[PDB]
Image: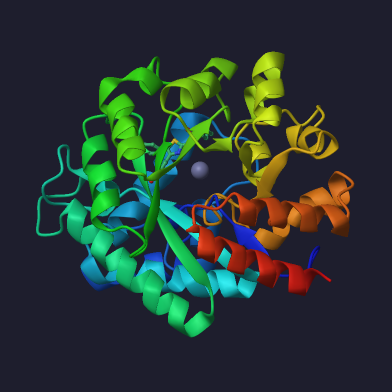
Amino acid sequence: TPAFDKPKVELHVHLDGAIKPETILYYGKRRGIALPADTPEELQNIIGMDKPLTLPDFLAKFDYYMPAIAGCRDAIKRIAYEFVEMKAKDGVVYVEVRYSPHLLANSKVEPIPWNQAEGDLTPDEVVSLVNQGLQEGERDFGVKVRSILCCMRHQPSWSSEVVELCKKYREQTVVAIDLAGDETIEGSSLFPGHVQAYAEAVKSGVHRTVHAGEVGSANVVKEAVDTLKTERLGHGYHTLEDTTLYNRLRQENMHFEICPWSSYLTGAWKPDTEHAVIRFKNDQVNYSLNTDDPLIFKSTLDTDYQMTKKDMGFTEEEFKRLNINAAKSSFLPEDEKKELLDLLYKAYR
Ligand SMILES: CCCCCC(=O)Nc1nc(-c2ccc(O)cc2)c(-c2ccc(O)cc2)s1
Ligand SMILES: [Zn+2]
């Protein structure tokens, strides 16, 4: 039953919310971290969702699984390897994947993530292993992979390690910075650790994306654009609350990272209304379709397309239009960006 059986691209998906239950539950055994269940199927039920949660309830899910994988050096490279296959099974020819170095680390990170004890595995080593997993992954499954390192809203003191990690591992495989986390923290956009991590990126031409607009206000989005200088938005749904902001960003041909299934499940979208993507579709916006976290949302790429295929009208034409846009909007070098594009064109006709 796949809603769109063509090659796809995906620009908004998190490593740490795309681990197989099997693998989480594997490192749980392999190292003594007691999880809330012992066969994969009920993990995917506990560590998964089907109503709007609360925000507390959502973050706590991260408190379950993460410490099985974080701190373990091979679970790292492994979730990365497993990630890439997960995508070839979706039909994706190009993915940028994101995650926070920090939150798979247990050494040289204040504060130590997830309640872990100290350690041996630094933020910087984290990225290295992710590169390996992902780029072996590329070689066997046939996906083009870049990564993207996430700044965290509630930790602007990490942010500098993030842009500089970005610079340290550039195309190999890192292409962009992000800002992610609770976008509802008061003033987190303009916290100086972040404003400067983003000005560093401009400076040293690392590409940029931001979650804004998802669960937070139009002003979150403008801060993103005007102050952190994003090239793309993470979700951006609330953009439509500010008509000039929207209008301008339609003039600017900005890229919105839509996540349709993601958004219902978060409250981000109110099940009564006109889904924002339907607007973006009717106004010809530059958006892309994305799962965001397929673990928590017990989902796959096809699920997102299915939601819109059958709940919101979307045609094959449209589906194709948006992978196009997605490719165009990628943080790939320009030579490779047009190579993606021609793949997509030959496959699309
Ligand atoms: C309730 C629905 C709202 C959804 C929107 C939201 O706030 N998203 C978030 N993403 C992460 C996140 C980001 C990157 C990452 O690598 C892992 C998680 C959060 C996090 C979760 C736990 C935490 O300690 C801090 C932020 S909170
Ligand atoms: Zn996200």
Residue 218 pos. (x, y %): 59, 18
Q: Examine the image and state in which quarter residue 196 appears.
A: top left
Residue 325 pos. (x, y %): 68, 50
Q: Examine the image and state in which quarter residue 270 appears.
A: top right
Compared across the picture, whether 338 is left or right of 140 comes to: right
Residue 292, placed above or below residue 27: above
Instruction: Check the image and name the residue furthest to the bottom.
Output: 140
Tell which quarter ligand 1 is in. Answer: top left
Along the viewing direction, whichever of 215 and 60 lies nearer the viewer: 215
Along the viewing direction, whichever of 176 and 102 lies nearer the viewer: 176
Kindly tell me whether residue 114 is visible in this rendering.
no
Residue 258, placed above or below residue 294: above
Residue 237 pos. (x, y %): 65, 30
Q: How is the image coloured?
A: rainbow
> Which quadrant is home to the C terminus?
bottom right
Question: How many badges with numbers are in the image?
Answer: 0
Compared across the picture, whether 312 is left or right of 169 comes to: right
Kindly tell me whether residue 347 is visible in this rendering.
yes
Residue at (27%, 21%) from the top-left corner? Answer: 192
Residue at (78%, 50%) from the top-left corner? Answer: 307
> Which quadrant is home to the N terminus?
bottom right
Compared across the picture, whether 212 is left or right of 242 comes to: left
Residue 311 pos. (x, y %): 85, 46
